[PDB]
Image (cartoon, rainbow, N blue to C red; front, side, top):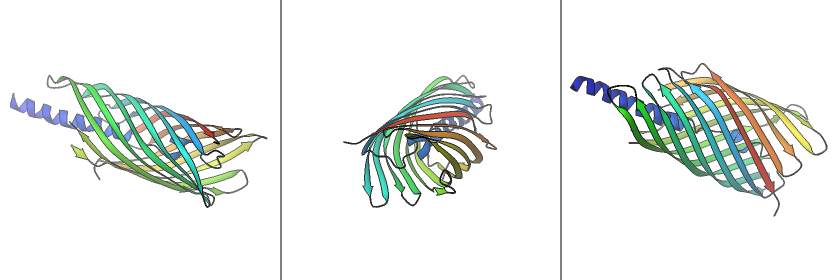
Length: 277
């Protein structure tokens, strides 16, 4: 009757929202994860592919897993002591999520543009704007709600800056700060905001025509459903490899602790081909 339906309605609105916010959070990236190392590339154009597979968990019995496949193309402009990459990208995501109240799958596509600036000083920025469309198909385990299909979408803007400080010829530390903001609308209009501050340190090995950089990162991250507060420490290890002049590979694994929502495991990989005209 009315009381059960109102309770149901409340649970459905909370669920729609959790899933919508989850779809946004899942897309939050950073320069190294998407693009790998962009320093000192001898090539005026590039193509890249990035894959991410990972799992998160939170309260309410929440657990999810996602796969992200992204590809992009850019041009490099050398302008004084700045290398500027301007590019475009397409994205796809498949996510499986469940909690005490629901179980289901979201399939998404999106795309956007980015500009990444790498300075001879060691400074860098990365700015991105993208669109993400989500198709959600979920069982609601409550109020005879059954199977529910609904769509959401969002606008995403991100700005990250950072600065590489060499300690020696082959080691560095790189503090970083990022802020991501969005407008999320689904069948709610909320404006999430996620921020991160952190440090990566690195050790580079090399031979005559290859290099391999081992990386360790530790970051503070906070996230707001509406610009409902959560925060966590992220811990990552990675490598970035160069083979000759044209091919790079990046790999990063990550986990978080202390969040209400955590990343329990995630492996990110990307390959970049860079080429002279």
